[PDB]
Amino acid sequence: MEMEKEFEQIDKSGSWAAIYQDIRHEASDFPSRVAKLPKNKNRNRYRDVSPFDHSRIKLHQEDNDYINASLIKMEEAQRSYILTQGPLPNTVGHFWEMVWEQKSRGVVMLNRVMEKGSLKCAQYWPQKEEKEMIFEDTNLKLTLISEDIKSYYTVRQLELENLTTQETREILHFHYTTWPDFGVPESPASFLNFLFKVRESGSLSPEHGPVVVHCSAGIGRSGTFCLADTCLLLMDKRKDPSSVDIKKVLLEMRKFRMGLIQTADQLRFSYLAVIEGAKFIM
Ligand SMILES: CCn1cc(C(=O)NCc2ccc(F)cc2)cn1
Image (tube, rainbow, N blue to C red; front, top):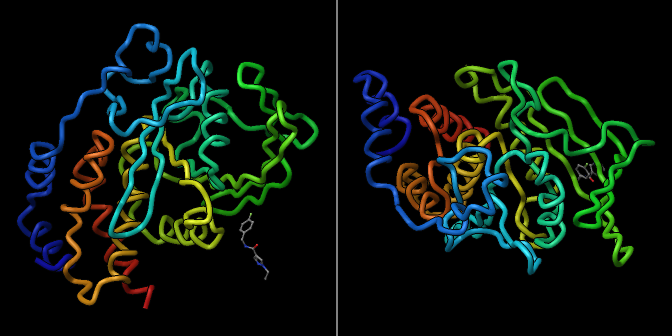
């Protein structure tokens, strides 16, 4: 079926939970043996969210190459994404090592450091120009260059230096700051505006390594971001845009990381975002 009318048909019939459970039943199951090794317990935020072995990002280190991060490679859309958890106190250095080694231009953050009174990820970037951060375990230096605070999101320019080679690179930090503590946003308008700002920066384009996108577990909000982006790109590429099937795209993405889209409300919100976004594109 088309999307907008399939949408109204699920609303009128109140069957979002049943649609979402079908997706959960059909989703791929692949091994994640490296994630479950005992030496990696303090590298995982949640025991039930792990990268598959076949698609995990490897750190370029011989001691321990593990990080909780997955490469989502979308062949028809010609887009790639790295989806990862919010960094932990003992993985902030690994996080920036990955950004460096994978040649990413942008980092997309969809959570606040504290939500619901609890810490959802480490304070992993510097908050003042004159107070830079040094990650001694991976030999990197990170400096805040500029910050632009808007009503729904903040954009930061950062300098990442590899202290071993003295090479430097400019990294863009796109921080969506207004996702509610409970539920999903009422309108997708500010989320779509944010997606378009990431696109306009070059961070999603083939001349750079894959964008790095995270929230607390790296599957829920993060899944919503890449699902909406890929669906809208496919609607621009194909002769028949009504042929784009959001449930099929989501199942393709779940071949590369488990659990993408965590609730039926997030599924409905993803439909809403793609529907409204397709009208603005034209
Ligand atoms: C009219 C001149 N102009 C150039 C840009 C530009 O560089 N856009 C890409 C970009 C986005 C966010 C960043 F932080 C840095 C770079 C915007 N206006």
